[PDB]
Amino acid sequence: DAVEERVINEEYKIWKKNTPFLYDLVMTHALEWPSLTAQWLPDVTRPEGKDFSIHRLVLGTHTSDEQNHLVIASVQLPNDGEFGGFGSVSGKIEIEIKINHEGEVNRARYMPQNPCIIATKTPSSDVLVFDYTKHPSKPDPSGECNPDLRLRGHQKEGYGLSWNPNLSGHLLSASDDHTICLWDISAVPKEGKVVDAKTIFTGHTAVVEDVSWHLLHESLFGSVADDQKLMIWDTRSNNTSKPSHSVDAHTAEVNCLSFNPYSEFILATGSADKTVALWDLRNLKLKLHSFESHKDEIFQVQWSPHNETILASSGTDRRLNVWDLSKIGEEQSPEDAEDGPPELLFIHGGHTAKISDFSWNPNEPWVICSVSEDNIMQVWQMAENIYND
Amino acid sequence: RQAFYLHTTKLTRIARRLCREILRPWHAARHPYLPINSAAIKAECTARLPEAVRKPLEAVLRYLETHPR
Image 1 (spheres, chains in turn orange, green):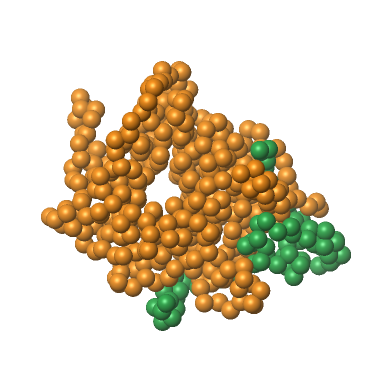
Image 2: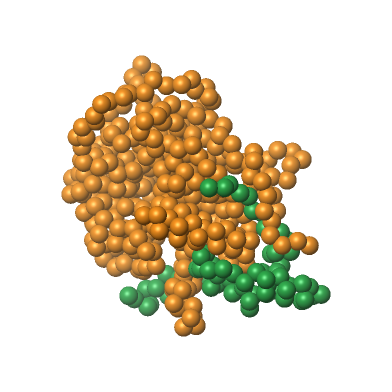
């Protein structure tokens, strides 16, 4: 409604004026179409003589009446007596590559063993794989399908899509029938362009939302679904109708999970129940912690690639929260208690609409890129006096 | 909505530390939509211009498993 829009606009203006005191870096950019996915690629190029480096993002498009694109964008990031710091963004964020894509890009993830290969998740149960070096960087226009109706004929598809970082070409996805597909694209034939699943895991009784490989154990993966369950699977097991472990993770749909990159035992899940949960694989009958502060459903949760005790969460609400595990238990004044628990390190208020995805920059600490339904992409870094204190 | 860039100045960075008691970063960090008292900060910074180790994950897990929910 118009009244809520005005409130949101007022709150954005306040945030924007506050930015120098809350952030060290904020870069914003309006995409032509909203992206439902965001992931930093690992490469950074450092052009000689310049006081910035170049970083790149995989994005996509959500449009229904126009030709969708898998997108690669470049971002210029600064190298390390007046207040503020505002400047122009012109030319700091540019689109390098557009690749025609049939459906909307629900999720896009690069293959860790060769980051030129991007897998994408469509609203159908197929997953597309693209090598962006094998396409032109600017496509010709596309011939759009104009169905006078589209009769939908499948339950939801969750966005779950994870490459195994220890087995090259092994790819998990959340299918549209409560199961999980596994493909192996290493040594696919030369002639064969289509590839069938090596395995189907059945177990969940509702829409599977997310899947993720374990980062160390090559045969372990986790999954979460609308059945309120977290499930740990082992590819070595002969029984693909039952997982190794099954947890009642939450009191509503579980939309996401993420393994902690400094500990083989720790992971986090995020739910429609408005909480993030902390789990230890050595004792999954006990939930270690619950991060409550979010006003709405959690859809994404991601651990800091640089700090073992840091994670961030996002979802339906326009805010993205950053949590510091090391502050769990700390004393607070009663006033600060009202603001939330001490483990809530930072609330990012820059977006004015639902946050679809976000990604921690793997190369510059504390840099995040977040994308929202309003078309906005923000690349930002909170003030060092908040994260060093 | 207008696009922008912010690379916070060295002076603002030191002002944030100097005027810790006015800014209250711990509080501000959880209140994006409250106006920060920048005037007060700028004043006290210009006036006072003539002058962190983290717990291991292991330790946080030890704390948690000894303070159950």
